[PDB]
Amino acid sequence: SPLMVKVLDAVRGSPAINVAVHVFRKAADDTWEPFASGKTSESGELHGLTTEEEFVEGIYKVEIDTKSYWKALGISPFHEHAEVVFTANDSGPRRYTIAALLSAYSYSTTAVVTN
Amino acid sequence: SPLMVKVLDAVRGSPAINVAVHVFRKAADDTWEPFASGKTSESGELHGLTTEEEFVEGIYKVEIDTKSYWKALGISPFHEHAEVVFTANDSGPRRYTIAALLSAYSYSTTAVVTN
Amino acid sequence: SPLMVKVLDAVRGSPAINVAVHVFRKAADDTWEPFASGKTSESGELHGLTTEEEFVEGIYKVEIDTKSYWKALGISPFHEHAEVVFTANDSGPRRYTIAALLSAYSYSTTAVVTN
Amino acid sequence: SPLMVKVLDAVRGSPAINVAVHVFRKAADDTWEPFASGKTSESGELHGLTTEEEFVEGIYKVEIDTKSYWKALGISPFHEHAEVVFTANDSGPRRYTIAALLSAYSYSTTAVVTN
Ligand SMILES: [Cl-]
Ligand SMILES: [Cl-]
Ligand SMILES: [Cl-]
Ligand SMILES: [Cl-]
């Protein structure tokens, strides 16, 4: 997959397991099409999201459903979810990894772009 | 204002000055109404966004327009913007501060809820 | 004070109140002298740490005692403390703000350097 | 290795490659013994740091030498280094992963503790 997502838990110090993740592509015009989705594994990683064939240039939104993750662990968190929005360019990097770190009232995300 | 937003710059180590910020409220149903907006000051803070009269319970989205901030500083960043989405509850805290820390390929946000 | 420290709590979504903070200066040579210290206020901020007279060039260590903060709130955290180490240059910025965001298993810090 | 360290770069959006990492153990008493060290690989990961035989209970310091990393990439950063200090307990988790995310004026670290 040219797009991978990895999620960590900063409250419990663990991979974020079984987190739902949705990818949308901005169709032109001008709304968010469901593009790909899945749930993180025991390592907190979500593999096989998409393929080079399906992953074309465009604006993508990665929605990590942090709210249900926390409730399943006994926590009612601040955020509804975590969102990451970016443009995929073919001149850009071949592989994108979206990494997220979750707390009850905070989150950080970073993009790791490689070849 | 019961809602304040503060933005820092982790690449240059400065307040994020003149960043555009938009707040939307999820109207029922089921879209994002423009609710309030403004630009951060020299301290990277955005004051007077709204009032207790206008700020009712609901789901709010705070969109920080990180892309134009970075381009104005000579940087073409990864993210289109930074988004923070949360529910305001009247049983909840009287004041919400959304703090964001921006990098070219990363951002973190935290909510500071006080009385 | 040319040095200020501000600490936030990402688990509870609050300023980090009454956190002990120690500043050391690397004496030449080659150990850490106690330079200044204090406890954050209700806003999570530590003001009046030092003065322009006392704050000379050198290597400084800011130790935030995150462990006792968390235990006082009923949490046994991962880290012993949070440390930030940097060089103050007179050609550099007049004011340094060290901002920290604490979780049970994580912390981030950023330096905000201004005039 | 029961201890692994992974480092990401938030300015360039890449694994942090060839970063020097030092682990010290607080000998009793009361100083920091060199315990283990190495340099991150192309994935930004540092494997084979130590073994279950050598990794006993105690207080450990992980020093990531962020300054030379940045200079090698043409950047003069704020921090001298990134430090992470924690207690290893045998009742604790079998494996510790220290993850760090670096910017010029900021860093975050998180501990991922697993079995
Ligand atoms: Cl709910
Ligand atoms: Cl563009
Ligand atoms: Cl203890
Ligand atoms: Cl130097």
Image: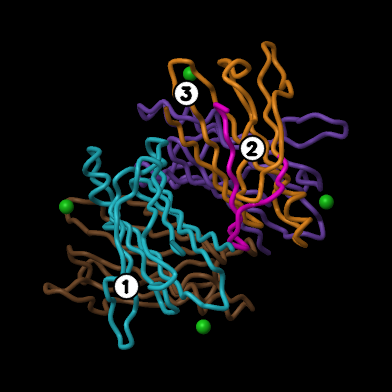
Chain colours: A orange, B purple, C brown, D cyan
Q: Is residue A74 magenta?
A: no
- Asked where in the image residue D5 lies, by quadrant, the reply is bottom left
Secondary structure at badge 2 equals strand
Amino acid carrying label 1: it is: Val
Where residue D88 appears, x then y in whole percent? 47, 74
**Which dot marks residue A94?**
3
Dot 3, how many residues are within 10 Å of its Cα: few (below 14), some (14-19), or many (20+)?
some
Whether residue C4 can be seen here: no
- The answer to whether tags 2 and 1 share a subunit is no
Q: CA distance from mark 2 to mark 3?
A: 21 Å
Residue D44 place in picture, x, y as percent: 39, 45
- As drawn, the residue found furthest toward the left would be C29
Q: Dividing the picture into quarters, in which one does residue D43 lie?
A: top left
Q: Residues within 10 Å of mark 1 (few under 14, many from 20)?
A: many
Residue type at the position of mark 3 = Arg
Q: Is residue C50 left or right of residue D106?
A: left
Q: Which mark is residue A83?
A: 2
Q: Chain of mark 3?
A: A
In this view of the protein, can residue B70 be seen by the observer?
yes
**CA gap, disc 2 and disc 1:** 37 Å
Label 1 chain ID:
C
**Magenta span:** A1-20
